[PDB]
Image (spheres, coloured by chain):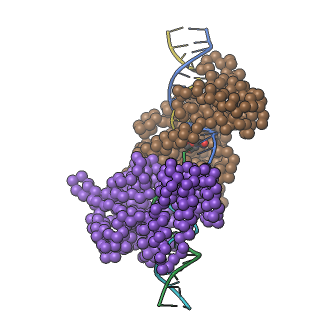
Chain colours: A purple, B brown, C cyan, D green, E yellow, F blue
Amino acid sequence: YPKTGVATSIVEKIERAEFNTAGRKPTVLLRIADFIAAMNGMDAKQDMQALWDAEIAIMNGRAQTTIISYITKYRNAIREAFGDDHPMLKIATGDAAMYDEAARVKMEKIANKHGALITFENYRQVLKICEDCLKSSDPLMIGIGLIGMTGRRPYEVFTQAEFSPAPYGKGVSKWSILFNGQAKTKQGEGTKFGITYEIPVLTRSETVLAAYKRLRESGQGKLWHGMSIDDFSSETRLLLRDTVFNLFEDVWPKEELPKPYGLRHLYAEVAYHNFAPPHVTKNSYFAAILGHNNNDLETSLSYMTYTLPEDRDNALARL
Amino acid sequence: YPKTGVATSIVEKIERAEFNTAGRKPTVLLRIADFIAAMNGMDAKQDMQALWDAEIAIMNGRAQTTIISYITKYRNAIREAFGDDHPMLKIATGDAAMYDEAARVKMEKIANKHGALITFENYRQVLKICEDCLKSSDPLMIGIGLIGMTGRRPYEVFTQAEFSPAPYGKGVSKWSILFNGQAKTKQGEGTKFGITYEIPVLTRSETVLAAYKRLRESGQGKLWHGMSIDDFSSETRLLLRDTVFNLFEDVWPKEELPKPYGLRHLYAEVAYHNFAPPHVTKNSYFAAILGHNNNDLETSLSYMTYTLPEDRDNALARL
DNA sequence: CATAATAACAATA
DNA sequence: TGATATTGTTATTATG
DNA sequence: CATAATAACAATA
DNA sequence: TGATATTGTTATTATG
């Protein structure tokens, strides 16, 4: 089903890491590599269970969230090396209790958000800053700008986004564009995978599109194009983190620090406040503009983070 | 654990039904009664499985939602008759697939709601009608009135609600009261079971409280007091249905028919529109006023049903 | 003498 | 109703 | 001659 | 991460 095979992505990573001139050892990837190796020729389920047990034991002392992520790394390797039918996929898994608990923690944090939204007092400043970034010659700057003005995920904006003009009857839409290249999504109906769909933008569409074409045409943009999430991460993440931190440090709400995804959160609040037609709920509207699954109203809870000072003002205008 | 016992509630119902002068036969309750009987002395799991299988087979041809409800009836009987440790409780259950599907259907309908809210054009009329009902001498009328002005569930208002004045510093709150007697809730932390808590009212608290005391003091109110859900249902439900239908038929939004629970839905929309402080989301606010569990933001999706014509007007006031 | 580079470690949607 | 893909933070490594 | 009463049947939160 | 409690609709029954 079969009993042999290799998780090639892991191995290439190990081989490249063999001659770095700095950095941590790839101990986790090495464990995975050896685990897949030891599986080769293995046919008894008890053997498989013993091997996984050894693994799980190593992992103890890590955070729950870490452990869960690692189980994903292993399972993705087993699938890579042996396929979808390997009996180890029923064995190498966390128990139901760990996932249940994970979900309890997630949901509690969110409910705390919903109870105490952050007033984003200088949101106009932040949006203008992003707009200013759209005219920068530095493609990282353009990219930040796009995350704020379009609300796409960094990985989307930088590596795989397709933007196009959205028609408005006989003309082109001024406040919205077409987007393709939704991440965190596999093929399935009611999924936006490889689906093109209209989204609002927080500045003139012409600007956004122009700026994106500059991004895609720069040398760095051609390098970024089509990267894996791993490569995108290691190539760009810490720099994007420090850049975004430096850009908004004295305008960002004092409750939190400025993080790239904040632009996506803020985007949704702002677009809802400006564009939501009246027969739609906040949940449904977010989930629409954010490319969430059909009948997925729950992922939208994650994004209710800020309250605009105008809303805060006039809700205070009672008696 | 043990092998003998009786589901007394079922049996009393059968015995009383023995001499009605009208009405359907209690065939379902009789099946349950016989099933519990046949369980007496039964010790082998295969025997138990055979008995449940026979049952499930009878039930086929009913709606999924019906079937699920019936499985609740049976399981509640087993628990009543033999306790929580009886091995039949692991056998008499729907499969995971049925519950999963149930949830898929529920969630799809809700997402359709969220996409197409109903504009409750005459909501002011409806609320005044409820207010007018608060001064009626007929306790069913007072009760309807209370469901609209307080958003409590019919079963709550009629049989077990405790209302009290809510203090406001040194005085009594004018727009809110204290409520105890939350239904659909078992003891557990982060549950409002036997918990008293402040809720908004859509007319002067003094009125609401006065009217409720009249309700509780009428002969019919003393009869309603402390009823089981079954008795409340059979005593009052069809009348409350027809009364509510006749009361609002020409003011209720034409998309649906006037149903008692609509007052609870409308209540939440209206109270949010008038009272929600600005650092709270719609989800968290509903779940608060509706007595939902802590960190329960999902039950609140069910209530997003209507859009107020004022909201609809000024969201239309874009460009 | 100390710090950039890298992956482990971790949280979020 | 089963067990993921992205974003965010920090410890450890090699290096004139 | 037909209809109120009752529980089955069903959906919702 | 297991398998409920309420609200809403209709078929069937007994009955001068």
Q: Position of residue B253 (x, y in %)?
A: 43, 39
The answer to whether one can see residue B295 in this image is no
Q: Quadrant of the N terminus of chain B?
A: top right
Please indicate whether residue F3 sits to the left or right of residue B273 in the image: right
Q: Nearer the viewer, residue B188 or B81?
A: B81
Hey, which residue is sitting farthest left in the picture? A170
Q: Nearer the viewer, residue B99 or A69?
A: A69
Point 57% across, 45% down: residue: B150
Q: Position of residue F14 (x, y in %)?
A: 62, 14
Q: Nearer the viewer, residue C12 or B146?
A: C12
Hey, which residue is sitting farthest front in the picture? A41
Point 51% across, 65% down: residue: A118
Q: Position of residue B232 (x, y in %)?
A: 64, 32
Q: Is residue B14 above or below residue A116?
A: above
Please indicate whether residue A267 sits to the left or right of residue B68 in the image: left
Point 43% across, 61% down: residue: A269
Count of residue discs: 0
The answer to whether one can see residue A18 in this image is yes
Please indicate whether residue B314 sits to the left or right of residue A119 in the image: left
Point 68% across, 31% down: residue: B46
Q: Position of residue B222 (x, y in %)?
A: 69, 34
Q: Quadrant of the C terminus of chain B?
A: bottom left
Q: Is residue A28 above or below residue B24?
A: below
